[PDB]
Image (tube, coloured by chain):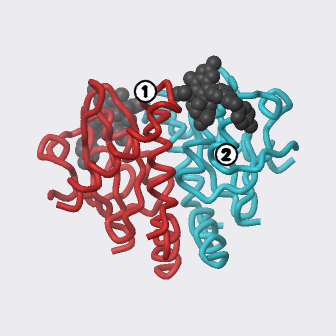
Chain colours: A cyan, B red
C-alpha cells in the first residue's frame, strides 16, 4: 500500500492535466502538458519517483501501459508498471478547485498547482499531505 | 526545522538549475529553467509548497528576496520568506551525478531529474528521502 500510485489524465482548456494519486492517502501531484504522450508520461514518472518511494504505478490506459518510453522510465526508476468511481470524483473535485482559483491565475499551470496545494492541505481530521507522510514513515 | 527550505541556483549548458533543499534532511527538488526570474521562482515555490509543508524559505539572493512576484507566491502559499559551504558541495555533487548520467539522457531536464532521484535515494544508513519523511512525521 505505501508505494502504490495511480495515473489519471483529464482535459481542460484544450490542454491535458496529468495526475498521480497516492492510493492510500489521496495525496496528488499534477502537471499541465499539451497532450498525453509516452515521453510526457515517462518524464512525469521519473520526477515523481525521485520525490516519493514509488513501487507500483497503475497506468491510466493501455497506450501508456504499452509505451516503450514509459516502460523504459519505469525500468530506470525501479517502478513495477501495472495495468488498471473515486478517480472520476477526484477529477471533478480538481476541476471545481481550478474554477474557484482561475481568476487569481493567468496561466492554467498556476491554477493547477494552486488546486494541488488546496487538495493536499484540505483537512478531511488529517490532510492527504499528513496521511502520505505518516503512511510512508510507518513503512520505514 | 521540519518546515525549513533553502533555495539554490546553479548554471549548466547555458541553462539554470533551480534547487530547493530541505535543510534538516538534505532532500532536494530541482527544475531546469532558461534563466532565473521572479516568475520562475514563484512558480517553483508554489509547486514545492503544494507537495511538502513549507514554513520558511531562505531565498538564494536579494533579487528573489525583493521580487514582488516571489513575495506574492510566498503570501499565497503561507510561506515565511526569509533572507540568507555545504550548498557549494551539493551543487558540485549534483553536477557530478548529472555528468555520470548525461549519456543516458538527451534532454538536460531528464539528466537533472535522474540526479534528483539518485541524490534522494543515496543511503548515507538512511537516505535523504527517508530522513525528510521521518522528520515531518515526528512533527505531526
Ligand atoms: C506581471 C505578472 C505576471 N504574473 C503571473 C503570470 C503570475 C502567475 O504566474 C506565475 C506563477 C508567476 C508563473 C499566474 O499565472 O497568474 C502571478 N502570480 C504571482 C504568484 C501567485 C499569487 C501564486 C499567482 C499569481 C503574478 C503576480 C505577481 C505579483 C502579484 O502581487 C499581488 C500583490 C501582493 C500580495 C502579497 C505580496 F506579498 C506581495 C504582493 C500578483 C500576481 C504576475 N505578475
Ligand atoms: C525517441 C526517444 C526520445 N527519447 C527521450 C527524449 C528520452 C528522454 O526524455 C524523456 C524523459 C522521455 C522526456 C531523454 O531525455 O533522453 C528517453 N528516455 C526514456 C526514459 C529514461 C530511461 C528515464 C530516459 C531516456 C527515450 C527512450 C525511450 C525508450 C528507451 O528504451 C530503452 C530500452 C528499454 C529498456 C527497458 C524497458 F523496460 C524498455 C525499453 C530508451 C530511451 C527516448 N526515445
Describe the element under mark 2 as helix, strand or loop: strand
User: Would the CB of label 1 be found within 8 Å of ligand 1?
Assistant: yes
The answer to which of B79 and A38 lies nearer the viewer is A38
Q: Residue B24 at what x, y percent from top left?
A: 35, 71
Which quarter of the figure is the C terminus of chain A placed in? bottom right
Give residue B89's quadrant in the image.
bottom left
Give a yes or no on whether discs 1 and 2 share a subunit.
yes
Q: Quadrant of ligand 2?
A: top right
Closer to the N terminus: mark 1 or mark 2?
2
The residue mark sitting in front, 1 or 2, is: 2
Q: Residue B80 at what x, y percent from top left?
A: 27, 60
User: Would the CB of label 2 be found within 8 Å of ligand 2?
Assistant: no
* Mark 2 neighbour class, 10 Å CA radius: few under 14, some 14 to 19, many 20 or more: many
- B105 over B9 or under it: above or below: above
Residue at figure coordinates x 27%, y 24% from the top left: B14
Q: Is residue B76 left or right of residue A93?
A: left
Q: Which mark identifies residue A106? A: 1
Describe the element under mark 1 as helix, strand or loop: loop
Give residue A25's quadrant in the image.
bottom right
- B133 over B10 or under it: above or below: below
| Chain at numbered mark 1 | A
Residue at figure coordinates x 51%, y 76% from the top left: B134
Q: Which mark identifies residue A20? A: 2
Q: Is residue A44 left or right of residue B69?
A: right
Residue at figure coordinates x 63%, y 43% from the top left: A76
| Chain at numbered mark 2 | A
Q: Which mark identifies residue A55? A: none
Which quarter of the figure is the N terminus of chain A placed in? bottom right
Q: Is residue A13 visible?
A: no
Q: Residue A8 at what x, y percent from top left?
A: 74, 39
Give residue A130's quadrant in the image.
bottom right
Residue at figure coordinates x 50%, y 42% from the top left: A113
Amino acid at each position: 500500500s505505501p508505494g502504490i500510485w495511480q495515473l489519471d489524465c483529464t482535459h481542460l482548456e484544450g490542454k491535458v492535466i496529468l495526475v498521480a494519486v497516492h492510493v492510500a492517502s489521496g495525496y496528488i501531484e499534477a502537471e499541465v502538458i499539451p497532450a498525453e504522450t509516452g515521453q510526457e508520461t515517462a518524464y512525469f514518472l521519473l520526477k515523481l519517483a525521485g520525490r516519493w518511494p514509488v513501487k507500483t504505478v497503475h497506468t491510466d490506459n493501455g497506450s501508456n501501459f504499452t509505451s516503450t518510453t514509459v516502460k523504459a522510465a519505469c525500468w530506470w526508476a525501479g517502478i513495477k508498471q501495472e495495468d488498471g468511481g473515486v478517480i472520476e470524483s477526484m477529477n471533478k473535485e480538481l476541476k471545481k478547485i481550478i474554477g474557484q482559483v482561475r481568476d487569481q491565475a493567468e496561466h492554467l499551470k498556476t491554477a493547477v498547482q494552486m488546486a494541488v496545494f488546496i487538495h493536499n492541505h484540505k483537512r478531511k481530521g488529517y490532510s492527504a499531505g499528513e496521511r502520505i507522510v505518516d503512511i510512508i514513515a510507518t513503512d520505514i
